[PDB]
Picture 1: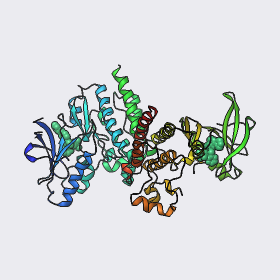
Picture 2: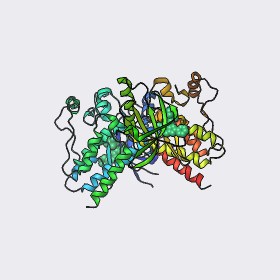
Picture 3: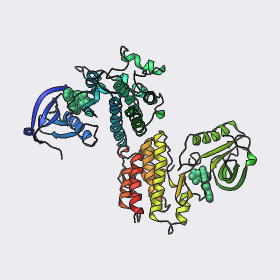
Length: 271
Length: 258
Ligand SMILES: CN(c1ncccc1CNc1c(C#N)cnc2[nH]c(-c3ccccc3)cc12)S(C)(=O)=O
Ligand SMILES: CN(c1ncccc1CNc1c(C#N)cnc2[nH]c(-c3ccccc3)cc12)S(C)(=O)=O
């Protein structure tokens, strides 16, 4: 059981918003002052909303990986809260932007490698993430990145259903079979990981800048692909282009991606 | 991959495939003057469609290179059209397990399940769905070596199929894991078939009601727990071949230590 008493939580400032409501930072008095992320649920007095929200905690509870945010616990009494591990250094895109001159290439490859370990782990549990993008990656330390909460990562996908959402469908990250037929598989996750690796090597710059979402599929179906980032090792760019094979059966699996990223990281650290 | 006919000595017929008899033979080449081979023949290869379908079976095998999958040696495109495959000298696994029933040690049975998991992890790495994983499709190269046989020769097996395959004709990497679970059960059962006495039409009802194949006599409990994971009704709850291979390696080490 992972039920937590509310008195042990000090609710701090709002750090973002999810589909169910504001996400706050806070402190969990367990150590007596652990930093946490707290998902809140504005419509949780409705049984169906409460079930959908608590299912997001059940989803995270099944995973245990060094590069995925951990579920700390739940408060099932109103207001219903989900307590997650806080990654103290924040969002990966902002972190890479601040260090666009500071961070070394070996650190960028390390983050792609750590993410491939988390994704090989999800693949081993037959879990399809659906939104592998730098926006859904957090920074725990200078040498550690983690995939953020999975419910919160579906914010862009879910934006089509929420009139007040600031989000937009993540077309620029999606595999063609996902855009065309709404098929989400372990192979479509590999395509998205390729785009995520491109974002990291680009220091948090978004893919297809200036291109309208509606114009993405036509470019991809005409054979267009994201260019090699400046300073990206050619072996790493060849890996990204394999992730973007139009035929999903031609894309590598995460076991091979992790092994190849480990070799690329070793070769970079050696020079 | 073209081979000259006189460089093949056609021996005895060892089985039959959809296109015709399969023979054992000898291939003489500068690499090996007397390599033992399996020869797939094609009785109606004068028909263009039959010839194309037959040669596609060689193309399928040509893309794979694994120690536990039979290798394609080459093809003879001139009539009669032949496909030359690596020979597994000890024959079919089911017959082999039946003969050596009292002879074979438990560690050997676990080794065969392990070697098959390495071949299947390799197919999974290339996103290839086999669809016909069963002891009938496994051959014996030596006392310490098994291989998946020709994929064309390997072509309803209701008693081996995942429920989503029976119900909706969905064949995925997860349905291959379900079949591999049944294959491991067959090996530990010394080549006995699953669900003996049950009509094919009655299998799905049993499966839906939570029934599963029982723990074979002398099967280590850790190995039976692995088989029961392969038979999770929800395909997303089934393990992948990388985990199966790692777990089978541990089970094999524990058995070899005794
Ligand atoms: C971007 N994501 C979010 N999406 C919507 C709302 C809020 C977030 C940030 N969530 C987290 C989580 C989770 N789960 C863990 N640690 C965290 N640390 C921080 C943070 C720390 C310092 C400064 C700024 C942000 C946020 C944060 S995610 C990765 O969860 O999909
Ligand atoms: C069972 N299979 C078959 N199905 C139909 C016809 C023939 C076979 C056996 N084929 C082989 C192969 C292939 N491919 C390789 N080595 C082989 N050695 C033998 C053999 C050796 C000695 C005695 C009896 C058989 C057969 C054989 S399979 C696994 O290929 O699907």
